[PDB]
Image (cartoon, each protein chain N blue to C red):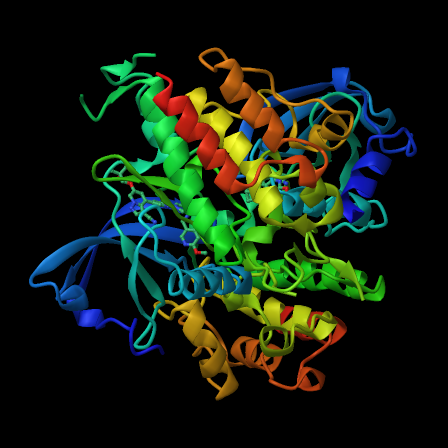
Length: 291
Length: 288
Ligand SMILES: COc1ccc(CN2[C@@H]3C[C@H]2CN(c2ccc(-c4cc(OCC(C)(C)O)cn5ncc(C#N)c45)cn2)C3)cn1
Ligand SMILES: COc1ccc(CN2[C@@H]3C[C@H]2CN(c2ccc(-c4cc(OCC(C)(C)O)cn5ncc(C#N)c45)cn2)C3)cn1
């Protein structure tokens, strides 16, 4: 079947560029864990012709993994090979010759954007009750970096499908990296959380760059609320009809008119009425120079 | 939605979490005036988490639709659902000992344990009986033209009097036409419980449920061990194709092992049917 073919292709030595010798990989602490998959920190010796040990993250399956897990991981590997951008997580390679399949990716010292934000406070060698302080300028900065990454992906004819604050990684110098390409595809029951999905994805199962834009609007909302939970107290099952009848999230606190207007436009019912990612970057670039 | 199954939300009180995984959760609950029982009845409630995808929603709805049609002493009882004024809540039977996997693993550290009268005291006779109750439930399920697809010790619940209840019907499918269920895309059943033709061919029949039953059997007689110990899921493709199967575990009889092996025949025709699995277990029991 399609998976046994990919598995077998993967387990052969066909891509010497991406194969990393297993003996050169030393696995450390767990960075995150779900039921069937795990991410650990690691050091990699002589990775990609680099001197000494490079700090990396390793993605791997757990023992109760289903074929849909195996598929997601292999599919991410195949997408990340074709991709190169400062705001997209970097793939270093894979170990396919010695035990479990391991994906080796760039290590993001702050972890997920969602985590980063909830540990922060909004403002206008000591110590504080919060990890850091963030201005609207930082938040606009974060959104712009993601929109750049997304513009690159849309130009590459790739639909991410799972855009959300938990899938953006925060690297050294607070650089945003789009991550989790398990569900991406080159442009039936979906595995994207309902609350981030575009109306046409929910009703017609259609996924395009414009449905990525809708998801981007939910992420913006997540950013300006510093890690809020979208549609709080509304059951995911109730959301279809609220959206169909034209309900949207209200303007959050500490959110400006111009910022909220951009969110709303991302959530237009007709995908043609939504901004493209270039328009989005433009809006953020303008906000920035204008303080 | 359905008159015979819709239950008044105000009559349902939710308690502690009994289990939660990726985007779904089970809570202990109590229901007032349930199916005309006086007073409160202790129940369990299955529901979605905030980050649910359409797949999880469709799975909860499909489990509801299946449990509506099936009634058997060894299949989890559905009481009803709250599906109107908010979140979808599935109301099912509460099983006091929890999952079979959990129950058997507990018997490793909780006396009297496995002995080779008390609820916690287990002999091989008790284990054969557990397997048999499950097989009778599966036999009925197969007669009702269903494939469970996700038969495993984690999906069997242990109720009052140590009765087995097949549960977790989210993935089960109708096979009235063709006697097979096939989908184009990848399944969500753990690789290690999947039949060889489910793995390579995306085909699910009662005979792939039989394969899964063999793995469950192995789980039972190892008292909740993990299948293909230390083998990566990805290695199962080549390993099953080349003819490797799990080894005979320690407190397993030759007849019991012969039954498992039969469940793991490459050719699905050569596997026993659930009716014949039940007969084999009946004979094992009475010859002791
Ligand atoms: C299908 O294959 C799968 C599926 C799921 C998984 C694991 N799942 C749960 C949710 C999803 C992904 N998960 C994580 C966990 C940690 C990280 C992560 C966390 C992290 O945190 C750093 C810190 C905050 C210092 O702990 C840094 N980095 N750097 C790179 C990555 C990556 N990738 C990370 C990213 N995703 C955890 C693995 N493989
Ligand atoms: C898609 O909809 C979903 C999907 C999955 C889930 C929850 N998932 C995780 C794995 C799967 C099913 N899960 C559970 C959790 C608890 C129980 C459970 C556990 C339980 O434990 C009793 C004890 C051990 C004394 O606490 C008793 N009962 N009785 C009925 C049920 C049911 N159902 C239970 C069964 N399945 C937890 C919820 N909704």
